[PDB]
Every structure is written in C-alpha cells, then in structure tokens.
Picture 1 (cartoon, each protein chain N blue to C red):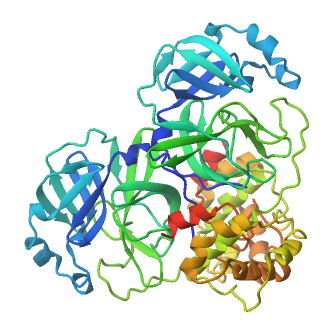
Picture 2 (picture 1 turned 90 degrees about the vertical axis):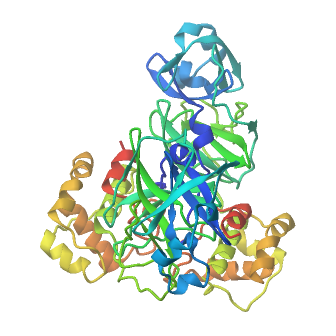
Picture 3 (picture 1 turned 90 degrees about the horizontal axis):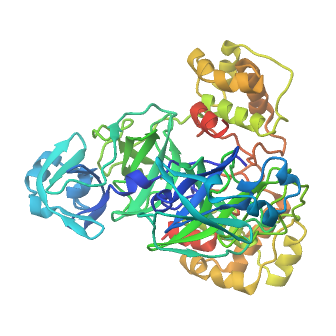
Length: 300
Length: 300
C-alpha cells in the first residue's frame, strides 16, 4: 500500500570493493584513496573468540590485504585502525568518489543499506536503527562491510557499516568512524541486546501516511494528553513520546487536519483493542520504520 | 524479518530524464539516442478524456518537447510513436547507456521500480505484477515515465513503464514497446481491473524463506494433492498451483527437506484457520511478492 523506499544506490555502488585476508572475505568502502572495512577481516575464525586487534594488526602486512574493485586489484600502501574500522591506504584514488559525510544517527532514524557480497552490489533496502541499536536486516556470509547511508541533494551521508550478526539473529554495526552502535563489540561472544521498543513517533507518522492515502477507519472521537498517552504506551513497550516528537509531526498534522494528540488517541485505541481483523495501508501490524521525514518525502 | 530487496539502481539512474510538453512534465528513459516516455505527455488535462493520439502527435513539433537530463538540455530531432510510448530522437547519445534488453514479464513476477519526479531519481523499491496486471506502488504527480527493471549479471532488463493511476488507486503501465499490461488504455476514463488473486507460488516461496530463517511454527503433519489444494485455494481467491509451479519450487524443497506438497498442506491450514494471532517472518499477513527466484537469491 505505502511502500518502503530506499535511496538511489548509484553513488554508493561505485565505492564498494572486496577485501580478503586469508579465508575471510568481506566488503569495503572505497572513498578517495581509503578502503574502509570491519577490522575483524584480519581475524581467523579462531581469532574472533577473543581477539587482540592491536597484536593481530601488527602481525599483518600490506600484502596480506587483497583488495579488488570489480576487476582492478588495488595495492594497499598502508593500514591504520580507527576504533573498530580498518583503513587500508591504496595507490589509486577512486574516480567515482561522491560528495560524502560521515554521520552518527540516533535510534529510530532510517537509512538505506546497499547489501553486497564479496564487493559486488546485490540489492538495496530501507532500514531503521532500532531503539536497542540493532538492525533487523538481511546479511549473509560475505555481507560484512556493507554500509548504510542517506542522501541529501547531492551528498551521501554514510551512517552505518555492518560488522556482526548476534547469536539472536539481529545485526550490529558501527558508524564510519568505527564506533559501535549500542553496547556491542566485534568479538564472537554471547552479547545481549536491550529490550527493544516500538518507535512511537514513527508509528504516528505512518498513521498520517494512511490518512493521506485514504485509510481513515482508525480515527475516533476520543482525545488524550501527552502524559496520559505515554503511561499507556509504556505498557505496550512503546517509546515515550516527547514534545519534540510532537513538533516533528507538525507538518503532517497541518496537511491532514488531525492534531498530533488526536492521532495519539487513535493509536491508544489501536494498542488496547487491536485491529479487529482489519488492515492499515495493507498491513495488519503497526509499522515503525517510517520517520516523519520519510512520510513527508513520499506524501508531498 | 525477511526484507524486500530492490536491485541496485546505478545503471538506471544515468538514463532518467525530464520530459515536458506544455504544462505536463513526466519522466523519460534515455537509451542511446532515444528518450522513451508515455505518449500522453502530449495531452493536455482536457485531451486525456478522449485523446486521438495520431491527430494530437501531428499537431506537435520537435521544439514542443523539452527534454532535460540533469542540467544538459537535449535537443529533439524527431518523434515517433510506438503503440503507447513516445520515442523522441535526440542529438546526443547517452554516454551512460548500460547493456539492456526489453522484456515483457508475466503476472506474478517481480521487478524494481526507480521512482523519479521530473527526471531526477527519488527512490527505488521492489514491485510485483499483480495477476490482474496492476501495480500497487507509490506514484505521485511527476511519477509518470518511471521504469521497472531487473538486472541479469550486467544487463538491465527493462520490463515496465508507469503510465496511469486508475480511479481505484492502483497503477497501470506498459512494457518498453508501448503495450499495456492488462486491458487498460491511456485515457482518463473509468477502467475496471479484474478480480485480483494472491500469487500462490510466491506465498509458498515466502514460506520456504521462513523455514530457512528458523520460522517453523506453521509446519504440520497433514499432506495434500495438487488437485485438492487448488479447490481450497480457489475459495480464498488464490491463484491455481500448477506442476510448473511445483517444479520451480524444487530448489527450495531440497534445501529445507520439505516437499512442495507438504508446504501446500501447511498453507491450506493457514488459509482455513488463520494465523491465530502469530506472525511469520515478522508479518501477520501472507506475503506474495517474493518469487521463488527472489528467495533463492537472498537465502543462498
């Protein structure tokens, strides 16, 4: 009904390379003359259990990193480690380097992931950073190093790089500076993610998208306050709604003629009574990976 | 849980242009020196009610078609009409023309749509041609001319071009030769699409993807025949399952150890009893826009 839309992947496709060290092959990000990759490419399957990356990196040479961009084989002329991201300096400046920034997103924000395997793009899809800093995406073997990004009018804002898949099936990664999102570490260990919650401001924006597209059955004639909505939202493991969230939902409220607190009263009834066998925008569940900015970008 | 994945849009991004004739602006496909666009760009809002395209095209000149590719303004040196697609011949060969084919897909098959507005790519998403030859996608004003495609190892198989949005909210289009999918015509009229049905072979492939990812609760210990499954599927408006569909599901059956007719018995119980408040791959509804080839491409 209202489809998840990913950013055009053209600017990022010309930056994906294949990085191999021993038996381990993953993906890398080829900005001007720097190939960014997860630092655990230097780790054997045994080393991942308790790696000492500083001692492991010293054991490594430039010739131990085989980098390939399509067919062109790139020659590493240096390697340095930012916190958990390896930086392999190459002889060749990427002639397809776009205008880019390195940003660290907040929990609840969305981004597009260019899933690639052994350096070649396979697909693109829209993600959302869960409140517990995990990603429910599709990452196979060979998927490590694939990056998440947003695009602002000519600029690619790189926001995420996939690093590990937790034993619970969820995925964890870092920003392009090597800092992990959440309490996770690049070590093959039992790591517990926090209690995940539903992004409340995203559900409200998705409900506004339903009203814009003619799906209006869930609108009611009860109202609520921000205080009393939250005490209901906390019971259903929904994130607390702030006045900042009410402010970001402003443009959608003016377009539909439905106050933000009026839509929250609609959401409160949906949480307490369910859907009663009906659907919203073709969905039987409440969707929470559409930010308010994602909705206004599609429903302009 | 198991995400819809769209093809990388890089090869198609370098072919999208903006075509304007009067007040009407839509998107065009710039292959070597040919800009493909819906022929109703020559129609005013009044002309769309009952257009005579042959008489309307004669009234038009080369200088009435303003084509823009980013900033470069392309000079039309000729216009010809394939059945419902306008072909504007330009002075400049597109230097970003990829290897491409023109294909006409079957109902139930999937493809990626590069949604663009006034010639500039805005997003990409995965579609499926409904059995009634409609598309439930996201097409705004300025969305006309955006193309659907698949990629086979270096080749872009263009399969669809958006033309109209029916009064019922669903979308209709043509192949790249100008032949409409379904009984629809490029005229602003009341047009009824057929009774839509669920793509049964796609639901079965999606159930195999659930088994591959550990979601196994729906597997049961009843069996069925292809004849007796269909007589249940016809009641729930599901497409009839053929032996060809059973053959395409072969690779997924061997990987999971579940016979195709065994999975159909699982689907029969889901149709008759429902989900009973549970989910499959994070979904409360049965998903039918994953072809068997889409599943094996993600679950390799």
